[PDB]
Amino acid sequence: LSALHWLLRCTAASAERLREGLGEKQLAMCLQRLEKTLSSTKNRALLHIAKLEEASSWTAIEHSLLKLGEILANLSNPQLRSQAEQCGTLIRSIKTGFPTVHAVILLEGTMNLTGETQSLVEQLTMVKRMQHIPTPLFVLEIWKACFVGLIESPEGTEELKWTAFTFLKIPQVLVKLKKYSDFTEDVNCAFEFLLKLTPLLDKADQRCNCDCTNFLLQECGKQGLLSEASVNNLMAKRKADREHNIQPNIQLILRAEPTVTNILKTMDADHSKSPEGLLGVLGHMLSGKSLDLLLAAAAATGKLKSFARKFINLNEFTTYGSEESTKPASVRALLFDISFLMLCHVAQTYGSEVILSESRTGAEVPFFETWMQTCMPEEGKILNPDHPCFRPDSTKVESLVALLNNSSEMKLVQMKWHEACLSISAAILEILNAWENGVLAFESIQKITDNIKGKVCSLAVCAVAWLVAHVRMLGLDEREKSLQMIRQLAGPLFSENTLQFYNERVVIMNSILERMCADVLQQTATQIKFPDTMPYWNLLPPKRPIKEVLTDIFAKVLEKGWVDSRSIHIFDTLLHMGGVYWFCNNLIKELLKETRKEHTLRAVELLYSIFCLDMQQVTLVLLGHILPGLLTDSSKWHSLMDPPGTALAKLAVWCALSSYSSASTRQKKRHREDIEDYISLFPLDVNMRDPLNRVLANLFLLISSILGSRTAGPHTQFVQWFMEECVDCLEQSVLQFMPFTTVSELVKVSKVVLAITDLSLPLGRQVAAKAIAAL
Amino acid sequence: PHWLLGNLVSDFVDTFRPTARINSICGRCSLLPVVNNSGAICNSWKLDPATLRFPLKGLLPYDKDLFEPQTALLRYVLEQPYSRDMVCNMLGLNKQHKQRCPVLEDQLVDLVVYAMERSETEEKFDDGGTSQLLWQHLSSQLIFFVLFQFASFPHMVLSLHQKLAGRGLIKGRDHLMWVLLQFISGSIQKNALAD
Amino acid sequence: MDLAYVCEWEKWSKSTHCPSVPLACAWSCRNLIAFTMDLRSDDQDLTRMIHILDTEHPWDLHSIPSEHHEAITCLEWDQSGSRLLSADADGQIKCWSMADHLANSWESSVGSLVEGDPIVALSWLHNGVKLALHVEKSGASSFGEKFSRVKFSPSLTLFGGKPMEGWIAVTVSGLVTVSLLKPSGQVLTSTESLCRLRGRVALADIAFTGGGNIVVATADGSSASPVQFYKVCVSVVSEKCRIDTEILPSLFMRCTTDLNRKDKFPAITHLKFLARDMSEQVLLCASSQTSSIVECWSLRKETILKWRILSATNDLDRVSAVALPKLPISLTNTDLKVASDTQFYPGLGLALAFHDGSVHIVHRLSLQTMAVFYSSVHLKAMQLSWTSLALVGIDSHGKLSVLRLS
Amino acid sequence: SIPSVLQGEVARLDPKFLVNLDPSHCSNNGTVHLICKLDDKDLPSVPPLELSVPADYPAQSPLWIDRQWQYDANPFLQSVHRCMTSRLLQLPDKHSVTALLNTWAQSVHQACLSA
């Protein structure tokens, strides 16, 4: 510190001699020793740890620096003035968009609308702390992602889910960000940032068919993100920029969320046990798009679970019967149909885990939960047709086949509909055996299918579920008969004996049967034409090897700069198909063949969000298999060059931190499938039976071994960068697993990993100055 | 070269590029003779019977085409009438010894599929039109070269099958069958039927 | 039963900081073991070397430096002993042949490539030769009575009685690929999806049938999803390979319909036909983290064709490797009787390694344990011999051991 | 930790040397690094002469990690460097640590007597 002060005084005196003179190379040499001392990382670290013990000499340092800067800036040089500016910046040293927030928001919109907001707030605060993001640009990227995903949404229920996601889930996220962190000024700044983007907002307004920025500003006013004066001048600006009969979906959703709450509170009590009122309200629900609007609002606002509990309890109430006559029982069976079909539609759209009760004290699990558990096809669920669930009795099933062969029932007055729906599988099994022997004609098959599908539509759904399981098990030539059964069960309407609301139940049932049969009718080319409703389904090309799909989608995502919704769905199917290791390895290969700084940083900011499909398993593969294979192989580390290598080290440390601090249904199923012994995989010469701690301990042993060895190459630069962004990215812990020999060795290879880690007590300077000086 | 020598040898051979450039008849790949049946073969047109390459003096770095099999010269000579002894003098065939020369066999097959292509172009605008003349000359030439076992029958037929597989060459299949009939009718009694 | 020798690497073990990989092992008809190991010293190509060990002189281990950029999934000798197929993750099937007819110099000129897709099953095509051993005619004093050919047809006969040689591989996507080697140096490749519903194939296996049909079984590891089956028929459209697939009856697995505690054993870990050319019986191995179940199934007809279970073990340790026999016994009822009376047990055993040291030689038909060998660390790869009197095995260390089974 | 043969060689040195361990560079993974000293009435060459004694001492004779920048900028130091390097060249194979210390001392003495 004193020699730096003497050097500053030498530059001041030599520059004064230069001013009096006007070869004065003394200034050139003085500045050369300034930049040669201060250019080293050792010396600037030593001055920074020298700062603490000698306070107020730094003031004299900077005042001499200011006078030096004046006397040099008056007499500029073609080379020395730039040098003096550089040394001044060194003594003081002692954007673009943010694609990751974009793709995280678009991922949560596409995959789990029904996820809790706290997980999303935790993930977004994480991303804001990893790469240090200002709050206006952060909220701007949230709004831009939401609007872009709304515009790119396919027409149908996905447009409803995206309108509910922007207008109902994102304000709650910003509210919890306001809690968990001067937010109104920042969100107002971000709204002005957004209101500059007139083409985005006009594309959105053409899809919304209204001013959806007006509804946004009134909604953020209601939540309290924005002051009212801000809201009014923003709406004035938006109207001025805008100047150059059916309700739109946003008004329907914003008014339909209070109807979700009030429909909960009024149908707690079965309309004071008036089932005709229930039939009227539920018939208004099955009128076009009203169910979807309620479900989108309830999903975006966290109340889908209570909605499912309410319809399940209604179903349990309407399962059995009482002493009824002909008319009262007709109403009760219709209540069973409406509750069943809406529960199947919920379970097929928003996943099955909102239907589960998650704790049932006592054995009294409802009928629909067990039926969905053991009998309904989902995406990753294939069913055993001769599971014991599909073989309840032999007693009731003969009563049921006699019931279906009697006439148009006439005995709906007491049916115990759960028993009937559980027995249809065995019933149509015996019908199929009778038709395969030949003892039943095709015309009687038509009569039985009409008796099934006519009075109550849920029977067709239960039968078609068992038929789909049974056709999936069969061979190719043996299928031909059973598919005809689906053609009659899923055919157009049987008429003239319908109870009530028949066409709407037919419409919902045709959707459910589409999503049940689609896979089996993909295996053999069979068109049923039930009635787009499956917008992201069957996305892969039929014959092309799957790495070409992966590299093409990643090339397009890099050249755009953000991840689409369709690209998210194909990336999910490839992660499920080729497995985690293949996926993560091929994406990292496609990273490592980039040569530009800009494209490498963008690729990493996208790949973090792509790996957020299953972050935990991807981190285990990444820090356990990919990085030790790149660091240990002697031929591989030429790939660890400067431009891709810094980016890869950033991605590894972001993945490590986000996995430590701590998501899709395929990934939940597959990690429940997975068996591995991480104690055996990483023998290692807190818990330490948690595999991530084991991978991190193994990786830090590898890093210490690389830093300690001879033959420094690009891999040593890699582990330097990894430790430096471990230091910079942390708040304070991933570095709890670092071996203490790394503390010594890292400044033997030189620097910041000391000067940050020490926490700067008076004794802490002594350990700092010991390590930093001693190379 | 080996990865330790590398440039040290490769550049060295590159400095022998001008000497090879002196010792090359320029345009040698595109010079063609006039086929006379007289014998007394000029030794310029002799090819290597193993690989259809020009025989080259030395080990110099010659130009890249001189290391290719000269199929153009051999097809031009086989397409000429009365080029029977000249093809033997080129490929060193001797007729005291039967050998099953393979590159001759492949060139004859490719000549047949070229005739089949050019017959499938039209063959009906001009009645003579060089097509049936080509098929007659193919009959005579291929009879001689399969008869003395310089090429062989069944490898020729199955390679011919692999060339015509899926190419969809059907308008003059009767001519190809006629040529095969010449071979079978010539030599059914000499060989087993499994040929 | 007994341990003949244990061959270990010297000082080249202690793989550090990089985790283990699964190993391959292949015992040829001539006694040459081809196998890969996790050496991991100064290079990862030490996990991409294919060691050839002549079993009479094990000290002399040749080490082919295969140019496989990812880890070698499958090794497979010929129907003779003269070529070796090796396929890794990311495509790249290579066909190693001897150089100058030395068993110490291998070089591959021929191979296939389905880039990016990991090969998960690999097999040579069947050349139509199959013989059966009648043990009850052991004294019959003529070799025609003891060993007799069983009229099997080769997949893809070409212009004569002569089979084409070639391989068929099944990737981790739905893709299957067939490569046919000509008598000339040419090679024809074709890939085609197995069925239209493209899905994960995490485990796969290949058997052949009479009639020249390949039967390929796929599973996606979940053990509550069906083990699907496809019939593949190869043809040459005069010059191009052509693959025709057709779905067969799938099966589900018991221990999922157990209903007491069905959730355990959630991973199918080994799928194996009982022998290639014995396409009607299937051995499956479900496993949890600690325990496992093997099962045998059969296609037998009555739905005409339908997979019914033969037998299953009670509960085991976690099965780490499985070796099926190669001796083609005649398997019918009289020969079962005489091989039980005169205690001939070479063709009736599978070996099951476990995650403790033990190895169980267990019956083919009803999987009851015939013998037990305690290692005194687990076998990560096992292979029985062609006469099935000795089994070779690579451990969870550098150790390679040959056991003799009486 | 430290092999017994190195401990005995250290215990039986001439009191001119004050050998110690090296905690500065990356050690305790490969060889044993030593900065000893020169404490003699005759003037000394730069003191560290960092010596890396590899494991299995009765083989792979230890190598002196060269540091020319300190031995430059001075004629005496350049001369001591030249003569000590030549004396290491003339040293027999499989030399010991005491051999390097003695040849260092005698090379310094030769540089003294020359100038």
Image (tube, rainbow, N blue to C red):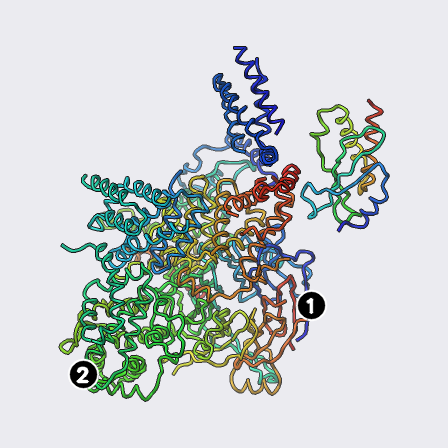
| Residue B83, x across and y down, in percent | 40, 45
Q: Amino acid at mark 2?
A: Ser
| Residue C100, x across and y down, in percent | 60, 55
Q: Circle 1: is it few (<14), some (14-19), or many (20+) Cα within 10 Å?
A: some
Chain at numbered mark 2: A
Chain at numbered mark 1: C
Give the labeled residue for mark 2.
A408
- Between A482 and A494, the one lying in front of the other is A494
Q: Is residue A729 above or below residue A524?
A: above
Q: Circle 2: is it few (<14), some (14-19), or many (20+) Cα within 10 Å?
A: some
Q: Distance between the Cα atoms at labels 1 and 2?
A: 79 Å
Q: Is residue C349 left or right of residue A253?
A: right
User: Can you see residue A604?
Assistant: yes
- Between A27 and C142, the one lying in front of the other is A27
Q: Is residue A323 left or right of residue A611?
A: left
Q: Quadrant of the N terminus of chain A?
A: top right
Q: Is residue A38 above or below residue A338?
A: above
Do marks 1 and 2 share a chain?
no
| Residue A703, x across and y down, in percent | 59, 48
Q: Quadrant of the C terminus of chain A?
A: top right
- Between B109 and A256, the one lying in front of the other is A256
Q: Amino acid at mark 1?
A: Tyr
Give the labeled residue for mark 1.
C5
Query: Please, what secondary structure does the residue beneath circle 2 have?
Result: loop
Q: Is residue A76 left or right of residue A42?
A: left
